[PDB]
Image (spheres, grey):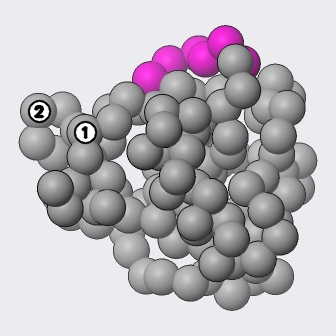
Amino acid sequence: KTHVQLSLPVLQVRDVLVRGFGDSVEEVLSEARQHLKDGTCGLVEVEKGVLPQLEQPYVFIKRSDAAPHGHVMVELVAELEGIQYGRSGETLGVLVPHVGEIPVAYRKVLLRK
């Protein structure tokens, strides 16, 4: 399937144990996609002071369209030293590995895979 319905655990930035997916734009997009498939991917909602507490490169989910079955259609955009790899809509948040942190909420997304 080109799209996959996911429910992403929303994590508080200060709870996150593994603060990024790796060391290159290509690695973090690779790792993010694998964690999304394996159900081991969390979402941090971006506000003032969040991104400096996470590791670059960042992986964002961004709205790709204006929402089947409650699931917002999203795609992945990476960012390193202020350059983004991809073009998409509004940021829903930054992706991180999920290693058992307790979420505050779930974000239903339809991931372009």
Judged left or right of residue 16, residue 95 is left
Q: Nearer the viewer, residue 94 or 3?
A: 3
Q: Quadrant of residue 101?
A: top right
Where is residue 90? Give x, y as percent: 42, 62
Q: Nearer the viewer, residue 27 or 61?
A: 27
* Residue type, mark 2 in image: His
Helix, strand or loop at label 1? It is: strand
Q: Are marks 2 and 1 in contact (CB under 8 Å)?
A: yes
Where is residue 108? Give x, y as percent: 32, 33
Q: Residue 38, relative to residue 84: is it above or below? A: above
Residue at mark 1? 5
Q: Is residue 102 magenta?
A: yes
Q: Residue 57, relative to residue 106: is it above or below? A: below
Residue at mark 2? 69
Give residue 23's mark: none
State the extent of the magenta-drawn residues as a range: 101-106
* Residue type, mark 1 in image: Gln
Which residue appears at 47% of the width and 65% of the height? 76
Judged left or right of residue 24, residue 104 is left
Q: Is residue 111 magenta?
A: no
Which residue appears at 31% of the width and 61% of the height? 113
Q: Nearer the viewer, residue 16 or 47?
A: 16
Where is residue 18? Give x, y as percent: 82, 40
Helix, strand or loop at label 2? It is: helix
Q: Nearer the viewer, residue 37 or 84?
A: 37
Q: Residue 72, relative to residue 1: is it above or below? A: above
Any part of residue 54 in sight: yes
Q: Residues within 10 Å of mark 2 (few under 14, many from 20)?
A: few
Q: Residue 51, relative to residue 103: is it above or below? A: below
